Image (cartoon, rainbow, N blue to C red; front, side, top):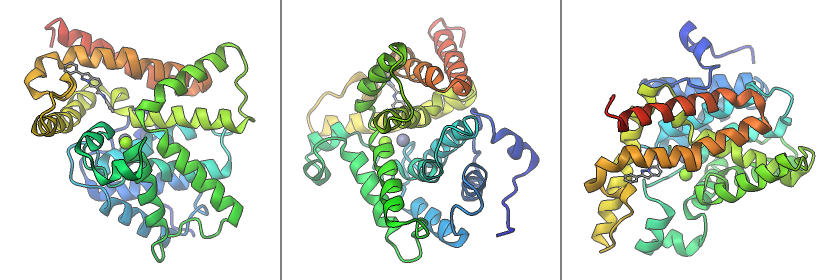
Length: 313
Ligand SMILES: O=C(Nc1ccnc(Cl)c1)c1ccc2cc(-c3ccccc3)nn2c1
Ligand SMILES: [Mg+2]
Ligand SMILES: [Zn+2]
């Protein structure tokens, strides 16, 4: 009850900033997450023993893949922490509880393969979940872990509050399917510009939480350049392995996943910043002005990729 988590001075200060990197010491990431739950939600939100047991079972159910790993889970949770702390009064008690957990769990048991590869492989999961295949699995794994003995961090919630938080988590995790992002952002852009956006409309809140989830999930593009550049290596390490597996199924992969086309990576990053990242943080900044630093950092990284193409690095 009177047991706060406290980080070293540099981490205590920089964890508040959007571009914070959680560092290479894996053993500190549980502590960093609990610290973030305590400050963004409260020391009362969760039973500490149950939370710690929940966190360590979530960690165990992330795989040793180059990018879609435990470090990604905690990184995405930190971006959500920064959004919530910069938007104090906008979010309900249940939303602050659910969204940090949603981010920690959003890629549970990821194999480093796209929905697309599962469909072409004819993976069992593609027959169980026809759309948003991996994201329905991530939600299923979250519910599984919540139902383990001593792992029910929501035990103090009423039956209707429990159903509400699990619905926040389900929608937040489904929203991380980038295929759904494009339509969600277009709808949010129209609602904001025609002035019909209403944060008391539950279907509108759902859309806004969806965009927050895309923003947190893509947040590697909002780090300082050296973090962004090195994270790109891990992202493409997965993409190229999927491309290899596409070639094993006798299917030429998209260039993004073809290691023979490494040379086109800089131009591929430009397309991604212009088609996905910048539009994402732009719309997020219009709806939630204090998230502007994410847009600024994204624009800084776009400029760095433009420099790579011009041979200035
Ligand atoms: O980074 C990307 N997607 C992503 C998804 C989820 N999360 C994160 Cl953080 C990032 C991304 C998107 C499109 C694209 C095209 C090419 C590309 C094109 C031609 C040649 C070589 C490569 N690379 N490439 C990378
Ligand atoms: Mg995912
Ligand atoms: Zn993710």
